Amino acid sequence: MVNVKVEFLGGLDAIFGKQRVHKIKMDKEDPVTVGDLIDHIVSTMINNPNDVSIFIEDDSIRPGIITLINDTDWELEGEKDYILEDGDIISFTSTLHGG
């Protein structure tokens, strides 16, 4: 199990109950990837199905949303392939033109 913190910023928290910060328990045994986390967020934390398209496009985070792992850009860490450790913080920030 890995315990991580997710942050939804830039207005994104509107589809996650208007709550910016979330403490997520991943029951999956190591290795647990950011891909697994995203899968979990989509199937368990988006309470209106029609909102999934805001977060996801193509089994992947929708361009315009900036993803950081512990305050570093996820493209520098393997994106979905990054392996989660206890205490990690994953932040997703909606932007206008950051595609």
Image (cartoon, rainbow, N blue to C red):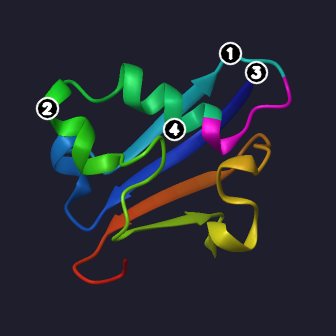
Badge count:
4
Q: Residues within 10 Å of mark 4 (few under 14, many from 20)?
A: some
Return the x and y of residue 13 as percentages of the image width and height. 24, 50
**Vertical relation: 55 (above or below) 95:** above
Dot 2 amino acid type:
Asn
- The residue positioned 80% from the left and 45% from the top of the image is 83
Mark whose residue sits in front, 3 or 2:
2
Quarter location, residue 66: bottom left
Decide if residue 16 is in sight here: no
x and y, in percent, of residue 98 in the image: 36, 82
Earlier residue among tags 3 and 2: 3
The three-letter code of the residue at mark 1 reads Asp
Quarter of the picture containing the C terminus is bottom left
Disc with the residue nearer the chain's start (2 vs 4): 4
Q: Do the residues under discs 3 and 2 have CB atoms within 8 angstroms?
A: no
Magenta stretch bounds: 30-35
- Disc 1/disc 3 C-alpha distance (Å): 5 Å
Residue furthest to the right in view is 30
For marks 1 and 3, the one nearer the N-term is: 3
Q: CA distance from mark 2 to mark 4?
A: 17 Å
Mark 4–mark 1 distance (CA, rounded to whole Å): 14 Å
The image quarter in which residue 90 lies: bottom right
Q: Which residue has dot 1 on it?
A: 27
Q: Amino acid at mark 4?
A: Ile
Residue wearing tag 2: 50
> How much space separates mark 4 and mark 3, taking CA atoms?
16 Å
Q: Residue 73, relative to residue 13: is it above or below?
A: below
**Residue 77, percent across and down?**
76, 65
